[PDB]
Length: 525
Image: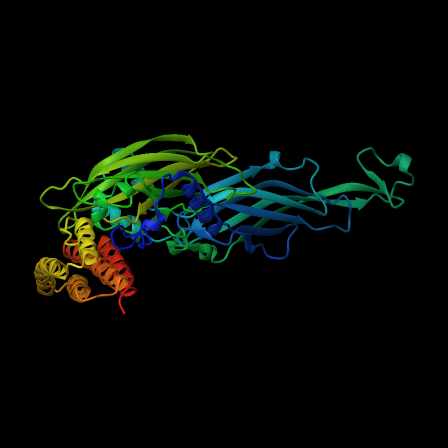
């Protein structure tokens, strides 16, 4: 079908979907690949000692995730075959810049070969995690549902802590000498060893404590989630006209999400309705997926608890819990979907709503210790307010029909009528520009002016539209004019949000503006 009445030329519209499942899975797969790591040495022991120590972890750790750590112990060969190295206890842990230690893991002598080792290599695998300031606040948030603007900002502004891993190996080496007083294997004691025509016997045991540490381990962690983009995931909301579109009822789109927390461990994919307007309803569907074999060669179980919410943002910037779903997953061995229905109830003072998902789980390390992880993922939606569309589809359809009926006088009447309405929308954009300048809010200023320029472009396209006698050219100008109005509508949403304490959602609206404005210009000569 068409661009001009249906807006089938809008890229967001071309991404709609009858069903969200397989696209969700795809997105998950795609995102997981982006987060796949290779092992890198984090550091090693002094290259002396009855044991060489090497530490390995991922090349990339996203945010506050837990991660597999490999420790490799080399027993170098000995001049004496029986001079076996025994390992009695290996201990690893994370240490912060205040000599505070976390997640200490201990392998006791039971773990190792009774007879000791000579010329050999040993691989130890464990799971670790840096310091995590937010974890318990997120856990509370999930349980009680109480989420303030304070916590909320804190989620996106807290940084990863500096840390290092250190390992301690303990045990003893056997020392053996030849017992010069034995002449024949027969006379070489049962415990001794005949070997190279001499009878070797066990002299002493020599203790060691070896210790290795990493350097700039924390340098493998990244905070920038820009890495976490899905191809074609959406931002914001389709223009409000799409509320009366049966064509789009019951359709989904994947949304880009903003992430914080243990993104390397598991992920959340968001599919939702593509339209979000005050006093209207939207569907959300969240996929929670463990991030496949990120802990390889380790294989810890992971399990538990979530809360998906919408948060009403009050003018000024305060937030309050709106619609919410919460429960337990058990073991997240398989992807699972969770739904949330948002009704964007409008009350005086209501600015907009945000959607957020919080998950809290435990990675259970083979030693039984349980390490808490959390994820926060915010669908990059935007809730629009009613801006009173001037170019309703019906009216656009009438106008085109007039063109065919050759009724240039009615085309003229209508154009003029529509232009009055846009002039009015401009008058209000001018009021926003005023407040924006008054409160010295740079962004609102830019947005409000943007709105004014968009509406102005639309008014101009309507003027030219009425004078066309090529058909496509008449369509093209109506279509440019339509998208320009949509762009201006976004800008106005943006300014309004900027002015009242939601600059984040404002930036989404403003970006959508730039997009529809550019789509418009593709139709202008």
